[PDB]
View (cartoon, rainbow, N blue to C red):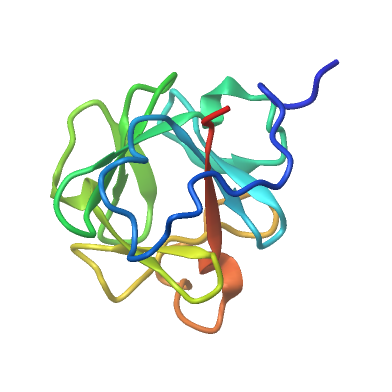
Amino acid sequence: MAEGEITTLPALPEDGGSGAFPPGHFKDPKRLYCKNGGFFLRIHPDGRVDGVREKSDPHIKLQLQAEERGVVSIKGVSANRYLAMKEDGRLLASKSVTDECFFFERLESNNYNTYRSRKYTSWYVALKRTGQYKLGSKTGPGQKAILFLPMSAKS
């Protein structure tokens, strides 16, 4: 009956944020919790990307990896696929990584993170309120769907 995996509750591990996010936190998976509509990102094995409020889904355990400075490659653990944004706006995942699998990460002044697309820095990643994936064409500033809260599953 224990909700979620190893519990969670609001916390703040490593309070030494005197800079940004140097290499030292991409060793454990990270749950992407969307503050808009409260929805956790979840990559299905079929590639279909969709968010869900069921934190008891071991499919939301995405393995992130820091590549260059500010660049971070996302990867699915159970899905075993790298997220990829198409050119029209359809988001999907594949076993082979590509140049569209990168996402410029940027932390704002609100403890909220923001993943911006690379091959398309003119659009950010954001889900809908019904748990569906918002087209990368309707995404943009003004919408708070960009306020993500990737919590590391340390403990």
